[PDB]
Amino acid sequence: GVPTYLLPGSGQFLTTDDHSSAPALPCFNPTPEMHIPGQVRNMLEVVQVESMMEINNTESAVGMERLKVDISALTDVDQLLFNIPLDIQLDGPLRNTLVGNISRYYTHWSGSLEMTFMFCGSFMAAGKLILCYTPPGGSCPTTRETAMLGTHIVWDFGLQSSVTLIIPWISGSHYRMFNNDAKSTNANVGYVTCFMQTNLIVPSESSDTCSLIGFIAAKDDFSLRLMRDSPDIGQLDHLHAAEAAYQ
Amino acid sequence: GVPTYLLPGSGQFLTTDDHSSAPALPCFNPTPEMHIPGQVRNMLEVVQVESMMEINNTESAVGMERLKVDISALTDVDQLLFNIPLDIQLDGPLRNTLVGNISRYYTHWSGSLEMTFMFCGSFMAAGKLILCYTPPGGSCPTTRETAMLGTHIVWDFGLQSSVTLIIPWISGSHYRMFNNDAKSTNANVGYVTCFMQTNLIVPSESSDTCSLIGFIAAKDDFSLRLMRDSPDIGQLDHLHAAEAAYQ
Amino acid sequence: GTHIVWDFGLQSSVTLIIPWISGSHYRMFNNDAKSTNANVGYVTCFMQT
Amino acid sequence: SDRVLQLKLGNSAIVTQEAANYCCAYGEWPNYLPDHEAVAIDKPTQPETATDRFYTLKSVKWETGSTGWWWKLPDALNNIGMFGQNVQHHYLYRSGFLIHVQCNATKFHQGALLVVAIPEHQRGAHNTNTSPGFDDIMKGEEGGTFNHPYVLDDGTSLACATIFPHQWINLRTNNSATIVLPWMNAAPMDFPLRHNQWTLAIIPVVPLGTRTTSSMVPITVSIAPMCCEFNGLRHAIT
Amino acid sequence: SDRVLQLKLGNSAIVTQEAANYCCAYGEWPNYLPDHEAVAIDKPTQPETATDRFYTLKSVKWETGSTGWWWKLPDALNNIGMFGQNVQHHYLYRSGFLIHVQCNATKFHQGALLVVAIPEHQRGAHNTNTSPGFDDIMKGEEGGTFNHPYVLDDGTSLACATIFPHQWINLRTNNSATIVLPWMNAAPMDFPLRHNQWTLAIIPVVPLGTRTTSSMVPITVSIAPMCCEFNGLRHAIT
Amino acid sequence: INFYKDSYAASASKQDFSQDPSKFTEPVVEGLKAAPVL
Amino acid sequence: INFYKDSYAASASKQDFSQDPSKFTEPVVEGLKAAPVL
Amino acid sequence: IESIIKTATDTVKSEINAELGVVPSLNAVETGATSNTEPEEAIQTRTVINQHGVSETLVENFLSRAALVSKRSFEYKDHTSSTADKNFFKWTINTRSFVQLRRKLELFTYLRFDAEITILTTVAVNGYVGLPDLTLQAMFVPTGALTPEKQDSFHWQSGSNASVFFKISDPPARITIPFMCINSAYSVFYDGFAGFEKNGLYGINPADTIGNLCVRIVNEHQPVGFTVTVRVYMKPKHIKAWAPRPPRTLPYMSIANANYKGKERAPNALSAIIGNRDSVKTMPHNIVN
Amino acid sequence: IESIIKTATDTVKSEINAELGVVPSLNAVETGATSNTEPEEAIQTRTVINQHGVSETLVENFLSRAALVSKRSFEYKDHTSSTADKNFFKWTINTRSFVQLRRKLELFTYLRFDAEITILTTVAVNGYVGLPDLTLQAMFVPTGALTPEKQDSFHWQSGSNASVFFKISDPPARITIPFMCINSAYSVFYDGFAGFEKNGLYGINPADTIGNLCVRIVNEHQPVGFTVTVRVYMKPKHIKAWAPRPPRTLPYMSIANANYKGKERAPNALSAIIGNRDSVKTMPHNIVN
């Protein structure tokens, strides 16, 4: 026979192993493949689809109310309307998004994001907003004259109901990490803020309060790395009727 | 299947083994290599860099004072100034050098060394020294008329502030051994001595005591062999905060 | 600003160039020294060592 | 030139002048079942214009506290016209669907409706271990209402429902949504009375608002089956 | 012909007539970040002569019991000129450094200074388990002083510090040391306010000595950033 | 390595790098001029 | 021997005999005539 | 358009744009399309040659992980007077009992895959003598077919059923079950009823159930009792996946349905998936220096 | 100049030199260059054809050694009333705890390598019956992610985490962790602070931490207690190394920093690294015949 020797690793069960194994049903003919719509072959196809941010993640916000931001006419200029933390790993407006949920199966991430905001006021509502991305390092800007030193888009409400704020991949390292320390230099993405640029100006017959819906997607320059168990699901017990599978 | 038999050695864990092993993170894409300055691919590149000998390894010599040799004007001719043991394995002036530390990770060594001495007196200081290498076999020379029968360089202090004493690979065997017995015929390299050739002659306004700094490097004919744990580091306890890695 | 660090050595001299640093093609020799069409700025010498 | 749209199927036609570039689900178009995918060997009936035509459901009223509406396909159509008659007389069916959802209001109204086609929308029940029964799921032409549209009545999320084929009716922008659905099933054909391939969900993400004098603002669903095939002819189930 | 040297960067120039053949760290020269190594996608600002110019630090006095001096880069420059302003207004920076160290004395003086650029000089504290804090490390323009230069304040050794890019100022021989530093980091760019790529260390290996009537002998550090890039523009941190 | 007679016994197939994200991100038939869509 | 699908799984790579000790021993740009350097 | 994507896309440099008629940052969300705004069109960019691989987010990599699907502890002893798994258990194979695998599979509507099954077995002495090297039989029985009702039953002769005999001492037992659905894909979710009447189960197509795993200890009982725990691990492979879905947000309640309750408070509550902050202007982890 | 060096350099014969202008033994240390004086230029030499290999001092050979990185002893017993590793431990992976590996890696500023991890497990009966062949689970959890807090916790189902199941009886478990830094190299030393505020750790870039190693015994507790010791060995491979450093001379104090104290007296004291001799003229091991 063949002289052989076993090595460290022999007989271990690695859950990520990649081996052929013994077919239990010899000569089994699987059912022939049928064309099914919507095949997904890389999960980065899923993160490129935009999905709703929960920007209004506040008490007194219940259910679907959390998925929209109310905007009102103001009587002071240059006001802050909302800000959005860019921490995917801790709990924020990005976590229960397509990009957020899939990315939390990974530890490392890179690439640009895009935020899309649809104005859902009346046709007769007019206004301009400034949507600012601040690279990390300082506090989140609270005044309009500080925030738009950063990356920003001035949005006019018009026939096109939506804009895109690109959050460009702005990072010293190739990847950022989904670690729990949000203030880490390998984690923190910075901030997104929205200020009034002019004002929400509406009819007496339009609603004086209008709603924005925020979306986020990854771009196709996005990559994910180092697969891990998602912290978005867990059990402390057996699920109901799991015992009946043994009876 | 294949008839096989296991052999002596099967299942052993050899710490120097060289095998492929199971990748724990399938399809992991490592970060792309970036050019970084100062890549080292062979440790013999490090031993060729000269570094300071601790020739003044005496009591009453504190810290950085140990890295220089004070030279004074004398009133007797042909005087000894200092000698340097060439025992890397036991504790001497060569141990905490680049060549010394890296070599103590090995047991066997071969090849030429070089000692470089920078005179750090004033511009106005003049003098000549004789730097002698004595091949082993006898006692270290204590008089100038004995020492320079061996390999030597007569150094004039001038615009060039430094000389090199080559310690040529002078050995019956291909390698010498870093064993603890310093008087062994497979270990002992011999001696380096420095004598006054003329005298240190200075101004009344220059310092009457001047300093030499000694350096040592290996040449590129140098080789190291038989890797071993370095006797330059050890622990009897766990280090501080090592337990917190488990908490 | 514009500067030269001078080491005293075998060459006993240095040159500080005062480059033509001006919004206008010419400056004027008028009596108002603080005029924007007149003032050239300053030359200072500090110890370096 | 993508705001106006005419959809002509059979004897039915729909015009809108406030569309917004119709959705073809997963970039697909409905087709008949090809020979290299077929299972049932009997020659299918393909009624074409008798069944592939727009059927308008009962309109629902959009109000301030509306949670949303759902209709299951083919269940909502299984009693309507010649489609319903072919469904009752055949064990097997196959079709795509052209869904058109209509909601207009004034230029002083606001509101956003998520119009999403959910394949295999297996519903969960709230706060119980008991699975939803037959009457909970099979509502017919009337359809149902979302209990918890924020989690899509299945413990997932409305916020990620844009992964499904969808459009929006933003009352400022458009008054209609159009979604073209292919056959979406693990099997090439299916028994129409016990399985629902698609669920049309219409969800108030931004509620109706105005300060004009109010009107009833209804939401109207027109659904055209597309490329209808039926196999396994027998008596009607009814 | 390697004793004399002029260094011209921007509006700054330095002449010496007692150099000794400048050090290019690891045989490298500073360059801008190439496209095949870049990460940050925004177009960087490259201020060139506004930032790539010699900045002279505060001189320190060389005395009999001096242990040595250190400055961390870019921390020593982060409040100086347009370099400091670009650092404060940008998340990311990248540069090399041209370091020129000046120390003259008489031909009756003696003394040797080790002028070494230490990459990632992570400092240790003496005789405690507590890591050095922020104020211990981040000294700014003033720099710090060696506590134990014999072990380089990190439990290693001065004697082996010649493995790093270095020159010597031997007062008999030369009056200046010049070290050219490339970008030295694991990442192509870095946040300037929380990380120091290089530490300039200047260490009295042979102390100052004369029997002339004494003078203040200062040591002067001039540092030119080289190939400055800045990414991630926003408001100033200050 | 796969010495079994049934092809489903093989190790995992991790080489299908084909993607079509436009069936999820752009499921209209008017390819949107990157220009207003409306 | 390496039957794994990831290249980092391979055994150690002990064949890179390239050296450039002059980036440590001679990091000047005036290559020193072996003649006084000064 | 379908293409081969091995790395994330590069960035091209871009310059100043000031053109009438062209507004690439404006979009219409109502069409259902994700925004096509490139970073080159929104900001002034550099050229980046991106070499970041995409292979770890391939659906094959994302789902070819051995995940725990079944964990049964049973007593190995003389069972003359017990009421409970008497030296054997049956397990109706499902992917629904352990929520890490379940949520990953429920990212998709349809899955086609072969199932590499790994069986880990461990033994403890009941509350010491040593651990015995017992032989086990794992027998694959199709769904609804006759399963053994005794340790010693003649059903275990396994004339046509696949059975695997394996030790405790040896490396876990491992076989591959082929893709065995009567359809071209499993239905991960099933909006339907399995029977032709109306009492049948909602959400459960039995076409997607692999079978019954019948696991005994082959050995006669020892004089002392042991507790034996059998862990079953499934790794999907040769995976095709269709129609991605919103991830599960609320905790699972049952293996039989998608029923939901949510946690008592945010996070992952019925009225609040994301945990609360004080206001929409409140930055929760704000850097303050 | 870069070249391929497989053997140490040869020596050429040399003759008498008496030339004005040429002083190859004179140098200028101030330039920072090491002396270029050849032995041929300093003494009269012979021709030597040197065949001494250089391969054992390749950085790959110098660092591809399996070195101990972690050693945890824990009790394997019923833990209902203990205060301590209750049949499992977590270990934040680091290279700082065992000084032989730490000093070798700290010869360099930047390291890029894959890590072959070998897990040796040994068991002792608490103070005899025999040693049980227990099954262990080593689960790789990324840095800061959720680690199990129980032996029996549902975190061990390991739906996406890499886990390795292995015996005591079998050859140690062995896997390879890839180079996983977000940078192109690990920072062996880090002159910086990890956070955007000023409370963060000095010297610790968490970008260079591999992860958490979560190791349990899979078995239920036996009626008697055992002490189980787990040894973890790391071997770097495919190594690139940059910017060599002065070796550590004083004893290490902490794994968290480069803090130093030195020994009480020479050798390796703060004021005296090399042990003392009586004078600079004293030859310490002088041959006397």
Image: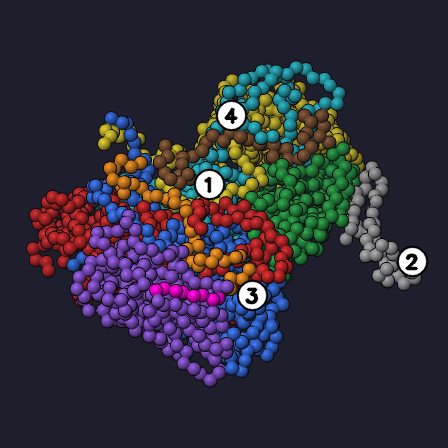
Chain colours: A blue, B yellow, D purple, E green, F orange, G brown, H red, I cyan
CA separation in Å, label 1 and label 3: 42 Å
Magenta stretch: residue A3 in it? no
Mark 3 neighbour density, 10 Å: few (under 14) some (14–19) many (20 or more): many
Tell me the subunit letter for badge 3: A
**Do callouts 2 and 4 point to residues on the same chain?**
no
In percent of width and height, residue B145 lies at 66, 19
Residue H15 position within the rendered picture, expressed as x and y whole percent measured from the top left: 62, 53
Instruction: Name the amino acid, label 1.
Output: Phe
Question: Which residue is labeled 3 in the image?
Answer: A131
Quadrant of the image occupied by residue C13: top right
Whole-percent x, y for residue I139 in the image = 35, 49
| SS assignment for the magenta stretch, majority | strand
Q: How many marks?
A: 4
Relative side of I209 to E134, left or right: left
Q: Nearer the viewer, mark 4 or mark 3?
A: 3
Q: Residue at x 72, y 42 (%)?
A: E208
Q: Which residue is mark 4?
A: I6
In this view, A238 is above or below D175: above
- Left or right position of H31 against D97: right
Farthest-out residue, bottom: D213
Q: Chain of mark 2?
A: C
Q: Name the residue: 35% across, 54% down.
A: A37
The residue that label 1 is drawn on is I113
Residue at the front extreme of this rendering: D11
Where does the magenta region start and end?
A: D3-10
The residue identified by callout 2 is C29
**Which chain is disc 4 placed on?**
I
Up-down relation of residue D185 to residue C12 (above or below): below
Tag 1 and tag 4, C-beta contact below 8 Å:
no
Instruction: Measure how far apart labels 1 and 4 are at the Cα level.
Output: 23 Å
Q: Amino acid at mark 4?
A: Lys
x and y percent of residue A160 in the render?
53, 66
